[PDB]
Amino acid sequence: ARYLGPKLKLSRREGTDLFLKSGVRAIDTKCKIEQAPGQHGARKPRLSDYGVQLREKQKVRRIYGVLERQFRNYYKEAARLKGNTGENLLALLEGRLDNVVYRMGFGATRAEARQLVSHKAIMVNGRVVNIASYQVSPNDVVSIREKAKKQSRVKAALELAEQREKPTWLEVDAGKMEGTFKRKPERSDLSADINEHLIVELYSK
Amino acid sequence: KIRTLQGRVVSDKMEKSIVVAIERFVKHPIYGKFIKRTTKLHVHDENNECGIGDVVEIRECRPLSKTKSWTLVRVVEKAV
Amino acid sequence: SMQDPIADMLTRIRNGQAANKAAVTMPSSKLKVAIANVLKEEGFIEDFKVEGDTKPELELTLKYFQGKAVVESIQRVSRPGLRIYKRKDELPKVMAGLGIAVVSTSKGVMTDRAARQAGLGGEIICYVA
Amino acid sequence: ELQEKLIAVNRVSKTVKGGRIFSFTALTVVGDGNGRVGFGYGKAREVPAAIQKAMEKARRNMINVALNNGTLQHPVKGVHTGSRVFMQPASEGTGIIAGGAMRAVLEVAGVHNVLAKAYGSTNPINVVRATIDGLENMNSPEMVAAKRGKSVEEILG
Amino acid sequence: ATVNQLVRKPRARKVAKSNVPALEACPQKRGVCTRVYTTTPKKPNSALRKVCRVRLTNGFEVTSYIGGEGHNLQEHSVILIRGGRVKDLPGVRYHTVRGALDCSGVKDRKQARSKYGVKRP
Amino acid sequence: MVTIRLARHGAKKRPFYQVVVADSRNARNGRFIERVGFFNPIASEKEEGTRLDLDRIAHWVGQGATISDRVAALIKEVNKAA
RNA sequence: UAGCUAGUAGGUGGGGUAACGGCUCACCUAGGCGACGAUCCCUAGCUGGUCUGAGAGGAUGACCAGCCACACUGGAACUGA
RNA sequence: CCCGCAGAAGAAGCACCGGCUAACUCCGUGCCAGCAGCCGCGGUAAUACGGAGGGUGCAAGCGUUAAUCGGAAUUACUGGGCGUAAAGCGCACGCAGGCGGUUUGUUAAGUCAGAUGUGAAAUCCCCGGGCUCAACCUGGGAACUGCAUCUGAUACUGGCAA
Ligand SMILES: [Mg+2]
Ligand SMILES: [Mg+2]
Ligand SMILES: [Mg+2]
Ligand SMILES: [Mg+2]
Ligand SMILES: [Mg+2]
Ligand SMILES: [Mg+2]
Ligand SMILES: [Mg+2]
Ligand SMILES: [Mg+2]
Ligand SMILES: [Mg+2]
Ligand SMILES: [Mg+2]
Ligand SMILES: [Mg+2]
Ligand SMILES: [Mg+2]
Ligand SMILES: [Mg+2]
Ligand SMILES: [Mg+2]
Ligand SMILES: [Mg+2]
Ligand SMILES: [Mg+2]
Ligand SMILES: [Mg+2]
Ligand SMILES: [Mg+2]
Ligand SMILES: [Mg+2]
Ligand SMILES: [Mg+2]
Ligand SMILES: [Mg+2]
Ligand SMILES: [Mg+2]
Ligand SMILES: [Mg+2]
Ligand SMILES: [Mg+2]
Ligand SMILES: [Mg+2]
Ligand SMILES: [Mg+2]
Ligand SMILES: [Mg+2]
Ligand SMILES: [Mg+2]
Ligand SMILES: [Mg+2]
Ligand SMILES: [Mg+2]
Ligand SMILES: [Mg+2]
Ligand SMILES: [Mg+2]
Ligand SMILES: [Mg+2]
Ligand SMILES: [Mg+2]
Ligand SMILES: [Mg+2]
Ligand SMILES: [Mg+2]
Ligand SMILES: [Mg+2]
Ligand SMILES: [Mg+2]
Ligand SMILES: [Mg+2]
Ligand SMILES: [Mg+2]
Ligand SMILES: [Mg+2]
Ligand SMILES: [Mg+2]
Ligand SMILES: [Mg+2]
Ligand SMILES: [Mg+2]
Ligand SMILES: [Mg+2]
Ligand SMILES: [Mg+2]
Ligand SMILES: [Mg+2]
Ligand SMILES: [Mg+2]
Ligand SMILES: [Mg+2]
Ligand SMILES: [Mg+2]
Ligand SMILES: [Mg+2]
Ligand SMILES: [Mg+2]
Ligand SMILES: [Mg+2]
Ligand SMILES: [Mg+2]
Ligand SMILES: [Mg+2]
Ligand SMILES: [Mg+2]
Ligand SMILES: [Mg+2]
Ligand SMILES: [Mg+2]
Ligand SMILES: [Mg+2]
Ligand SMILES: [Mg+2]
Ligand SMILES: [Mg+2]
Ligand SMILES: [Mg+2]
Ligand SMILES: [Mg+2]
Ligand SMILES: [Mg+2]
Ligand SMILES: [Mg+2]
Ligand SMILES: [Mg+2]
């Protein structure tokens, strides 16, 4: 269901910063990033065309915290939907509740945002939701319930969200822990680094 | 109108009954080529009116033996 | 022995183009003139005649733009060994609609583009890329 | 306007009195990503010396390709030796769904989305020539209008 | 070729035979076993390969390979059989399932234990 | 004897009843001539709850078809002037 | 598997059937079928569909629904719409 | 289904790691013991064997197995071939069969165009909706590439003309 292993190991293998071990401090400099995937990290990889596709797929998986079986289902949904197959893959991933809860700032990490969703804390349109995979539709209002509001894990985690880029597609109140998901996210708004084209190649063959 | 079928006679040597082939120019399902397929019916007629090798019109009707549910309507173009 | 005359016409065109040859004589017919007119009217062939009374010899005059020939390719579709009749909606479009398919429809021989708008199908004689 | 890339590298043998001497052959395809493509073969004693020798030939041996927006004009064949190669235009969605060798040449040419299948043999050299034959062959509506001397709109519309 | 020829005699599809006649699309099958023995493979290998003649339940008499270091099979002892050629012993075209029935697991294995039928340490 | 009756579709603990014109002898889920609206007991106060095409009912009940215990009450639920 | 068929193929006299009819008699004619594969042999419930495939196709007929068939094996009729 | 108890507390494998194909080393062994989907690994410095760590890939499942289609344009109707790779009968005549030069007239069988019937409901496909979310469920839409039926179009193909 989840990874629950060494999370910063996933960032060294992938190379780039995955926002797994983001948390309270801004930059890590606490792992020998890039040049130590494992014991054999100094080994320069030759890296084939199937390699770069699968390295790209696993990066987008490990950032958003999704497994291949559920991740493949997003591709099947993406292909059937209108527009571009690549843009729909990531637009569906960004509409998850544990991802939106992370983007609002109610969670220092996405695993904390996943747990906060799961732990009866998160509530949307006056209805409690436990599922991290919950597809957040356009024009909604995610929020924290009054029992778990202003607990010690959320207030420190909301101050981290000021240092973050902060999405344009969603808005946050910040006083009463109340969020508002407005429109669907656009390609150009977020990322500008993780390639979609290579993940469409892996699943079409 | 009545739902008749044209066809050329194969034999008439049975007393008051005639066997008639109906050529139909259907196409082949797979290969797309047009085939000349046959449908040999038994048909009723009063007396030995029609001989061998001539076109005949035929109507669907009451089953008047084992086989031979079709029945004659009229002759068109007699034997050569 | 000379079973399909129309396919033979389209080879004299195709082989005539390959030789960089100006004109292409052949035995005329009703359907030969119909096709050759549809080819002329769109602009593969540059003029033609049907000179003769008793034994008419239809000659075409093949078009050339550069050193290359105008007829890129031309092939018989509804040969006599296998006739191919297509419905209105099922009519083909050669080269994504920038080459033509000659099609004998009930209102005379015409292009596939003309057959769509006229609102009827027929025997597709040849593709002309 | 580089957009150069390698398809295949293959070691080959000669055989001489002493024994057998190995060399390497490259196969690189370069293009501007906007209607120019060019394969280059090249061969050398060492592997990296071959790819430079290939790339230099590829740049010179370039072919123009009149393509619509980011895709082909019409469905096109392109035989060469034992490789048949068929490839279809396709719509504004999708990507390059073609085999390796056949899609290195397509992406650097600047076609963003096509259907494609290599029939026959799939020898990396001969499929690359098969595609480029087909892409050189591929005529546009502006060419076809001028060739017949009719009209750009009356043909298309 | 020739469209008329095909109408007259259509394309006969190549009915490809199965590699493993265990019959009725069966995943596995029991075997009483007779003659457990050692056999030499083909050319580049050279070894003493462990193999047994399997008297199957349906009636067939085949040879199955005993994969893993050491075995408990002897004379009789009922074993389970799965599909898979060894590609060395000519004739042998089945594999004994280690773990199931009288065929025990390999002694002291750690890596890859579903293959070779061993539990956790 | 033709009869208008429910078909019982949908999941376990989550039923959904396709009111349908079928023969007496044929099964609940099985054969029929034509379905005529539906019914949902787990709908609650929202946009849609129950729908029943009354024009087709006149064709069958007017001729000679019985209405079952549940479907007769849905004709009362949908009302004539309420 | 290249020939098969004597109620076999027709016609009428009679006879039966809810009803058309070799369904069944009596005669009369001596045909009918088959290379567009009869007959014989092996295998098989059939379809809506399912699966795969770009599609043509190939495979398939668990589950829901229609039709057929069968009820310890082999006959038989009764009772009734 | 809604609230309260406690305290991380009760809850992670098992494939693989020579190439194909995402992922490395140390020992032990020495053409032996064993791996093997294909090529192929072992003869005393094994990345392929057994172990260990290290990794990688999936994870409530994972591998193996059998079974169908795919890739296989490797039965090719769309869409292959037959000088030397498998493949032109040793060569003729010829009935049935397939195909048939050229020009008018007429039928319309094929073909084409419209017509009404009908392709049971289900799934399959879009716009919706109810399961907390999905899976499931369901409302409508097209689809159901169907098969028949009258009316015409007559270029083409056939029938019949001279
Ligand atoms: Mg799961
Ligand atoms: Mg690699
Ligand atoms: Mg919603
Ligand atoms: Mg508390
Ligand atoms: Mg696919
Ligand atoms: Mg009719
Ligand atoms: Mg028809
Ligand atoms: Mg009868
Ligand atoms: Mg039409
Ligand atoms: Mg040497
Ligand atoms: Mg090949
Ligand atoms: Mg290992
Ligand atoms: Mg109620
Ligand atoms: Mg109530
Ligand atoms: Mg009742
Ligand atoms: Mg006699
Ligand atoms: Mg598919
Ligand atoms: Mg295919
Ligand atoms: Mg499908
Ligand atoms: Mg059953
Ligand atoms: Mg039915
Ligand atoms: Mg029983
Ligand atoms: Mg009984
Ligand atoms: Mg009985
Ligand atoms: Mg309390
Ligand atoms: Mg408490
Ligand atoms: Mg390996
Ligand atoms: Mg390699
Ligand atoms: Mg590798
Ligand atoms: Mg050392
Ligand atoms: Mg192994
Ligand atoms: Mg060393
Ligand atoms: Mg060693
Ligand atoms: Mg491990
Ligand atoms: Mg799996
Ligand atoms: Mg298999
Ligand atoms: Mg295959
Ligand atoms: Mg095939
Ligand atoms: Mg063919
Ligand atoms: Mg072949
Ligand atoms: Mg030879
Ligand atoms: Mg030969
Ligand atoms: Mg010869
Ligand atoms: Mg000779
Ligand atoms: Mg003849
Ligand atoms: Mg003629
Ligand atoms: Mg005429
Ligand atoms: Mg007249
Ligand atoms: Mg008329
Ligand atoms: Mg209608
Ligand atoms: Mg109607
Ligand atoms: Mg209808
Ligand atoms: Mg299904
Ligand atoms: Mg259902
Ligand atoms: Mg929906
Ligand atoms: Mg619940
Ligand atoms: Mg409906
Ligand atoms: Mg529906
Ligand atoms: Mg309806
Ligand atoms: Mg509508
Ligand atoms: Mg409607
Ligand atoms: Mg339906
Ligand atoms: Mg008329
Ligand atoms: Mg006229
Ligand atoms: Mg003829
Ligand atoms: Mg004649």
Image (spheres, coloured by chain):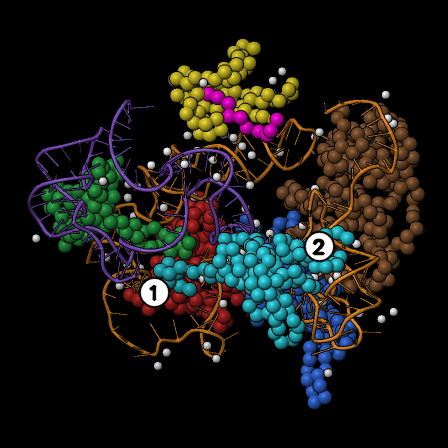
Chain colours: A brown, B green, C red, D blue, E cyan, F yellow, G purple, H orange
From the viewer's perspective, is residue A190 above or below residue A155?
below
Residue H31, percent across and down?
Answer: 70, 76
Residue hosting label 2:
E118
Q: Are marks 2 and 1 in contact (CB under 8 Å)?
A: no
Q: Chain of mark 1?
A: C
Q: Quadrant of residue C119?
A: top left
Residue C87, percent across and down?
Answer: 43, 47
Q: Quadrant of the N terminus of chain A?
A: top right
Q: Is residue A175 visible?
A: yes
Label 2 element class: loop
User: Which residue occupies 74% across, 58% down?
Assistant: E109
Residue hosting label 1:
C3
Given residues C74 and E91, the one toward you in this image is E91
Callout 1 amino acid:
Gln
Within 10 Å of disc 2 (Cα), the crowding (few <14, some 14-19, many 20+) is some
Residues drawn in magenta: F4-13
In three-dimensional space, the C-alpha distance between marks 2 and 1, rounded to whole angstroms, equals: 76 Å
Label 1 element class: loop
User: Which residue occupies 35% across, 60% down?
Assistant: E8
Given residues D17 and E79, the one toward you in this image is E79
Nearer the viewer's eye, disc 2 or disc 1?
A: 2
Callout 2 amino acid:
Val
Q: Is residue F34 left or right of residue H108?
A: right
Residue H137, percent across and down?
Answer: 58, 31
User: Which residue occupies 76% across, 32% down?
Assistant: A130
